[PDB]
Image 1 (cartoon, rainbow, N blue to C red):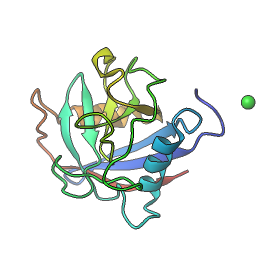
Image 2: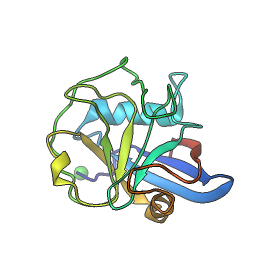
Image 3: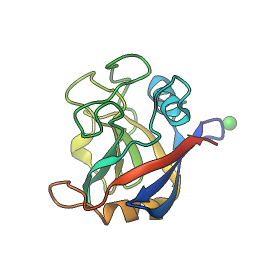
Length: 167
Ligand SMILES: [Cl-]
């Protein structure tokens, strides 16, 4: 669960030139170490690729803010530090409320770099998507991102991760 030894990472987010603030996230390395490590390394950029300058390409109010397509920047791409895809590590954490970080996928064992931040409980994603962290500060920034979304997910401003890293 939450723990002092878990890594902490951040995104600084902008919407068409407007600063939205910083999201700070704790990653459950103690539950899903491979999945947490992937996300952490993508935040620092240490493998030579990562989340910096990527966008939130799909935002559905009352559901998710989705980003992490670092290879195509449109929802069709993504890549992990382990290759194009990696396994669903476990489903020990459920989608019990807002502010959870969960891996996007297109089927079993197809995790890459795409992720969502939840805006609500989502039981239907349990045993389907791996939850690997939570927003510890900056949920206000997440609600700003939500404000630019729409029912089908298109966004009215380009929402970018202008800086990111590990605390
Ligand atoms: Cl302890």
